[PDB]
Image (cartoon, rainbow over all chains, first blue to last red):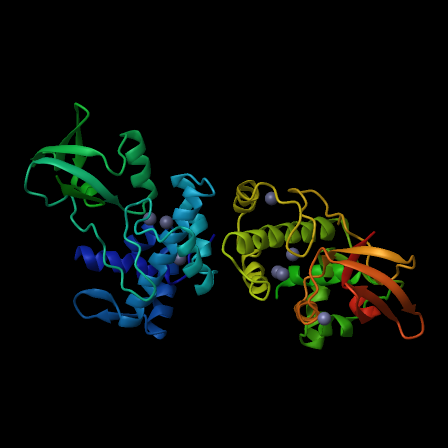
Length: 215
Length: 212
Ligand SMILES: [Zn+2]
Ligand SMILES: [Zn+2]
Ligand SMILES: [Zn+2]
Ligand SMILES: [Zn+2]
Ligand SMILES: [Zn+2]
Ligand SMILES: [Zn+2]
Ligand SMILES: [Zn+2]
Ligand SMILES: [Zn+2]
């Protein structure tokens, strides 16, 4: 399974939403591909008018890239809803399968599978599923990192991230869980939360990949 | 159309008593003449097929199970597209064609369970098991049958032209067909379905499978 150039658009998409920038080598890392590989992908994306090199902000999406990225998100999430709920895929299995299929599936297939799934609006990660030709506008944008108010929160959405999956397994975190934010340990650099009468410190690194909402 | 597509063409061209040529293959799948050579030459290197002056090309045991797996993928996908995504017959091929080349064995093996182990595809084609060689339950083609009587249309070839032929003759899988006469000189058969009579060239009769 080899991710094509287009997957760079999906990573740039969320980075732009979170309003932060990393190097192409760091993007290549989380993309599980060589650095010189991403350089060739971005090279192709520039020629095909999918991204532009901004003087200051780095690499940005063109309107053509937003559309193609929004389209990939809908197909990716619609496919993993089917794989998990119908074909009985586990969370650690869905990504690689939904990845190959999002590049080899007709619009008719996609827009009929939608009807088949009764028009789901969120994937197993809690990410919004936009309608045909609609730009992806996430329902859940609030990241635990930066959160000021203490009290009870609900875990509504997490990133499509294998490592984050294993973190949530070894800590028993599920979408929909009530976790009480006690404080932000400045010294530790971790948000201290309480779940089921058990304290856990969440490093701000992890806290940035999680989305919450208050009761 | 990758090399694996050529195997499915050689496999179903082997059912015909006629020997296989390069020029007829490029016609069957309507592609460049030397392109068939460029591809068939690759098949001969990997020992997927081999030359035989009596049949032209033959599928090796590796070619058999490899194409056998292809038919499995293709057909399981056909059952899903039609019974669950409500695809019509004119829509299923290109979709199933793309997916069979981009889907894990895990996907194929789980869709199989999900569909409750379907035994035949929309064309009446048999669905083999993982790693199991393909043996069609319905092997008897209309071209060749001599006994008179009432036969049942059990299976058809995956062919776009055959689809059109069947729907403009309102022919479905399951219809009772009575053999009336066979023209040995012309290579045509004469059948009857509910009083209505129809003439069928032997070439078309080789694309259809019947049983008594
Ligand atoms: Zn992709
Ligand atoms: Zn994924
Ligand atoms: Zn998701
Ligand atoms: Zn194929
Ligand atoms: Zn087909
Ligand atoms: Zn079929
Ligand atoms: Zn299999
Ligand atoms: Zn009629």
